Image (cartoon, coloured by chain):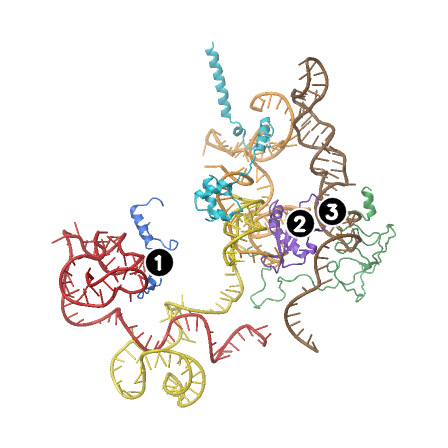
Chain colours: A purple, B cyan, C green, D blue, E brown, F orange, G yellow, H red
Amino acid sequence: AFKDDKAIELTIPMGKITIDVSKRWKCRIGIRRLKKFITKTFHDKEAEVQISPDLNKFLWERGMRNVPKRVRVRVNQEPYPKDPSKKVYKLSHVVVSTFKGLGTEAIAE
Amino acid sequence: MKLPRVKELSADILKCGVRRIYLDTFEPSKLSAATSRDDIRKLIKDGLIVRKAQKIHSRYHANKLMREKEKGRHSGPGKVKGSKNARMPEKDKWIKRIRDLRNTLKELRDKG
Amino acid sequence: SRKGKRKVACIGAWHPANVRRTVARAGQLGFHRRTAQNKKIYMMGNGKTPFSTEYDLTSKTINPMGGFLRYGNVKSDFIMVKGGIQGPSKRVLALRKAFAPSNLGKDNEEIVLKFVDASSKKGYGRFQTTEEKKAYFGI
Amino acid sequence: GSIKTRRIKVQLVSALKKNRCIPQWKRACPGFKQQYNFTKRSWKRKTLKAC
RNA sequence: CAGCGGUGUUGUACGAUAUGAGCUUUCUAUUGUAGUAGCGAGUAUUUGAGACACUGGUUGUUACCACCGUCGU
RNA sequence: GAGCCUCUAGUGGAUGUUUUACACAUGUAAGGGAAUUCGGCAAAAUGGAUGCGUAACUUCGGGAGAAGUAUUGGUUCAAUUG
RNA sequence: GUACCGAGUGAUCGGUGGUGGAGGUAGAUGCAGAGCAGAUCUUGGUGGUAGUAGCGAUAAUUUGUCUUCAGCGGCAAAGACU
RNA sequence: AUACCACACACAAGGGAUCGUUUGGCUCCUGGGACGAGGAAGGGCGCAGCAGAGAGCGAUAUGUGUGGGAGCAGCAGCAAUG
C-alpha cells in the first residue's frame, strides 16, 4: 500500500469542487469530481477509484440537487486485480461529530 | 430458470406484487436450480425468498388537524373557499328543524 | 422577428456584388493594444512607509484593509494616477514620458490631497483601520 | 381475439403449418436445387386476410 | 487539509432555563394530614451567537524527483 | 373523480466535456409610462369567500359579480350557527 | 478481353507478348429488327458533397457484485416518478 | 505540396458488359375438336420413415389384372415370394 502500509485519512471539500456545477444534476456530477480530486491528490491520473456503498448512501442523502459540505474518508491503495499494471484506491466513510481539528492523518492498519 | 421468473412465480404464491419479493444473495446457484412451483415453495419455507414489509404512511397530522378543527381552530374567513351554502347546506337545516318540531307536537297531542 | 434580433439586418446592396469591410460582423472583442495619453501623477510613494495629509492626521500606508482583492499588499514603490487604466490586476504596462506638452487648463493645474480611502474592497467597507474596528466592536 | 368462427380457425391452423423452412436432409439430395423457401412469412411484415 | 491571526456576508444556532392572554384541578402515601399538578401561540437569557467563504501572514501533518517523441551536434 | 403531495400496484439509457456567439422555453429591472407599432400584438395588472354599497336604459324578466370600497394567519377563550 | 507496335485523308484494318479454354474467317452475291452524347429518354450499377448534416420533447439517476465476454443484462442497497 | 487535387502505367478491390452455349419462346402447316344430376368446371382440406413449396393421389390417399424386367438419387431400411 502506502508508506509502511498505512492508510491515509482525509477530508474532501465537496462544496468547493462543485461550485460551477448545475443545480439540476449536482449529485450526479459530484461523483465524477470526487474521483478526480483523489487522483490529483496522489498524482496518479490513470488509476482506478472505488466507492464503498455506505459512502454512496451518505452522498445521496438529500437527493440529486444537493451534496454535503465536507466528508471524512479513509483511503487504501492496492494493485488493481483485473489489470495489475494499474493501482486502485478504495474509499471508506468515517463518521465524525465535528470537523474542527481534523487535518490529514496517516494511521497504521 | 432466470431470476426474473422466480420473482413472478413467488409473487403469485405469496399474493403480493413483484416489488415486495427479496431474493437472498449468498446462494444464487440454489435459486437458479429451481424448476417448479414445489421447488419455490421449499425455498420460501427455508427463508431464501422473503416478502418485504410495506412502506409507512402515518395519520399523525391528519388526526391532529381533525381534533383541532373539532375544537374550532382553523376555519376562519381566510381559510374557506366555498359558499356558506356549500359548507352548511340550507335545505338540510330546514329538514332537521321541522322534523323535530312536528315530532314534538305529535307526542304532546298523543299524551293529552 | 424570426431568426434573431441581435444582428445587422442588411449587410449590403446588390452592387457591388461583395460584402464591404465597413459592415459590422461577429468576432473577437478585447485583448488589444491601446495607449492612453497625458495621464497625471497625483502621488509617488512606498508600500511600507506611512503618510499623512495636512488635514487627515492619521498615519497609514496605501494598503486597504485586507489588501487588494487578488494581489495582497504593496511592498515596493508606487505611482498613483487619475482615472482608469487598461487591463486587469497583475498585467504588465509600459510607461513613457509625454510625447508633446498639453495646453489644456485641466491638465496643467496643481493637486492638493486632503483624504485617501483605505477601507475594504470586499463587501461594504466601513472602517479605515483595524483600530476603529476594534473600538466599534467590544474588546 | 378469443371469439372465432370455425371457418376462421381452420384458416389460421393451415397458415401455421405451412410456415416452415426446408428440412435439413433435403439439401444433401443430388437432384435438389432450392436454397430457401420463398413462401415463409412473418406476422410483422404481412397480413393473412383471414379477417 | 487543520489550528492561530486577518477581511467579509447573513442576523442571534441546538439544547436547557425562565416567563406567558387564558383554561384547568390530577396524582402518591394513607382517615386525617402531608405530598401534589396539567395544556398553551409567543417572548427573554446563555449568544454580534451559529453557519459559510477568501487570505500573496504564521505553525503542524500528508503528497510529488518520472516518462514518450522530433530535430541537431 | 380540479391543481399540488403520499400508500397499494407498476416503471427509464447515443459518452464524455462547465461548455463562445446566435437561438428556443423561462425569470428580474433605476427614472419615465404606449413616446413603440397598421393596430397595446405579446406581457403585466385583476382573481376565492364574507359584508357594505350599486347608474343610464329596458320587451319590466333583466342590466348585475354593474361600478366603488373593506375584511381574511396562528393561539386561548366565550357563544352555539348568528 | 488487355498492354504495345505498324498500315489508311478517314470511317476502320493488321501483327506481337501475357489472360482465356472451344470454335473462327477471306472473295462474290442474297435478305434486314443494320452504326448514338443528348430525348426533365428506359433498365441496371457507381461518385462528389461527407466520416459531414443529424441520431437527446417526456420521470433521472448513482454505487457494489456476478455473469456477459464485455449487454446502464441480472441481483442487492439508495435516489426519483405516474 | 512531404501528405491535398488531377492524369498515365503495374498489382489488389468493385461491378456484371462482351464472346462462346440453350430440355424455352414465336410463326407457318397438318390432325383433333373428346364436359355436367352416373354431380361438371372452379375452390378448400387431408395423405410420405425422416417432408415446407410444387408434382401425384383421396380415409383402399402406390389396391387388382395384363405386357415387360433390376434396382429404389441422400441416411436408414426394402427387393426374382418382383
Location of mark 1 (residue): D21
x, y percent for residue F13:
52, 53
Query: For the view shown, which residue lies furthest in the top direction?
Result: B112
Q: Are marks 2 and 1 in contact (CB under 8 Å)?
A: no
Q: Is residue A48 or residue E8 the one in the foreground?
A: A48
How many labels sit on residues? 3
Is residue B10 positioned above or below B77 on the image?
below
**Residue A19, can we see it?**
no
Q: Residues within 10 Å of mark 2 (few under 14, many from 20)?
A: some
Q: Chain of mark 2?
A: A
Residue B45 disc label: none
Q: Amino acid at mark 3?
A: Gly
Residue C51, by quadrant, is bottom right
Q: Measuring 49% from the left and 25% from the top, which residue is drawn there? A: B92
Tell me which label, 3 or 2, sits earlier in the chain: 2
What distance separates the C-alpha of mark 3 from that of mark 2? Answer: 15 Å
Q: Secondary structure at mark 2?
A: strand
Q: Position of residue G53 (x, y in %)?
A: 53, 61
Residue C133 in sight: yes
Q: Which mark is residue A73?
A: 2
